Image: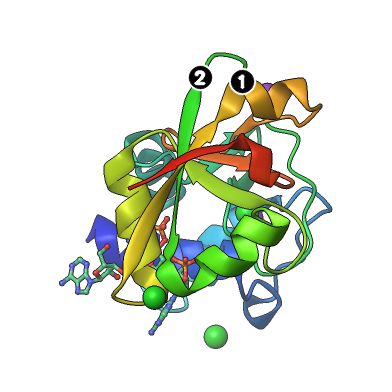
Amino acid sequence: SRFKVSKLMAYILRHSPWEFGLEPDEEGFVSIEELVNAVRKVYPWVTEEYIREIVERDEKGRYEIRGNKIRARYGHSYPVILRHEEDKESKVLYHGTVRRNLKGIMREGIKPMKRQYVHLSINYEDAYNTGMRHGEDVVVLIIDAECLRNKGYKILKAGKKVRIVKHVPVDCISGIL
Ligand SMILES: Nc1ncnc2c1ncn2[C@@H]1O[C@H](COP(=O)(O)O[C@H]2[C@@H](OP(=O)(O)O)[C@H](n3cnc4c(N)ncnc43)O[C@@H]2COP(=O)(O)O[C@H]2[C@@H](O)[C@H](n3cnc4c(N)ncnc43)O[C@@H]2CO)[C@@H](O)[C@H]1O
Ligand SMILES: [Cl-]
Ligand SMILES: [Cl-]
Ligand SMILES: [Cl-]
Ligand SMILES: [K+]
Ligand SMILES: [K+]
């Protein structure tokens, strides 16, 4: 299924490419031809044409292809430089988290966990679903993205829904849902 193969693509591209003999460049890209060979170790019926269709059809825009190179657009657990197109349009974004985090966030703003980027969403629904990852008592923070930009921070379009930024200062949080 596309779900099973996409789930494995995400794992390879975000988390364990070396396990499959792949060497991502500094931007997270691997050869799509070698990715087929890697995926075929689990699902031998996969074709390059199939992986390309998965990228084209993916609901979240999880993947990016340029020529012979493919990457996950977000979510990597190893260091990547992601020079995505800037979101200069969004006025308000959302960040899902757990209530226990409010104290630190109110003191220090939203910081990225493993350096790199803080994840934001354009939808309140996606942000809540995201916060459920870290526990039951989820709150969604409203982010004034205009304020963020004016403080000098670039918000980048990492997927159809996901937005990434280096840090969110406390002053840029306009509400809690
Ligand atoms: N044993 C493993 N444990 C943990 N991680 C593993 C494992 N093995 C490989 N990994 C990779 O290690 C990364 C983890 O961390 P993470 O990078 O943050 O990725 C998240 C998501 O990434 P994303 O959607 O935000 O882009 C990513 N993910 C989700 N959907 C994806 C897609 N279509 N294509 C590519 N990736 C997708 O799976 C991750 C979980 O997310 P979660 O939504 O809680 O679980 C989904 C579903 O699995 C789950 N569910 C249960 N049953 C069914 C069912 N019958 N049908 C459909 N869903 C079902 O019910 C939740 C609702 O969707 C990921 O790469 C993993 O593949
Ligand atoms: Cl393996
Ligand atoms: Cl990321
Ligand atoms: Cl909590
Ligand atoms: K990647
Ligand atoms: K921006």
Image position, residue 95 (x, y; %) = 47, 48
With 50 as the anchor, is 142 left or right in this view? right
Q: Read off the residue under disc 1.
A: 146
The answer for how far apart the CA atoms under marks 2 and 1 are is 5 Å
* Kind of residue at disc 2: Lys
Left-right relation of 63 to 88:
left
Viewport quadrant of the N terminus: bottom left
Is disc 2 placed on a helix, strand or loop?
Answer: loop
Residue beneath disc 2: 91
Q: Quadrant of residue 129?
A: bottom left
Name the colour scheme: rainbow
Pointer 2 with pointer 1, Cβ within 8 A: yes
What residue is drawn where x is 57% and y is 58%?
A: 75
> Residue 98 at x, y = what percent?
42, 68
**Residue located at (68% from left, 29% from top):** 148
The x and y percentages for residue 33 are 60, 53
User: Which residue sits furthest top?
Assistant: 89
Quadrant field for ligand 6? top right
Residue positioned 75% across, 60% down in the render: 24
Residue 112 appears in which quarter of the rendering? bottom right
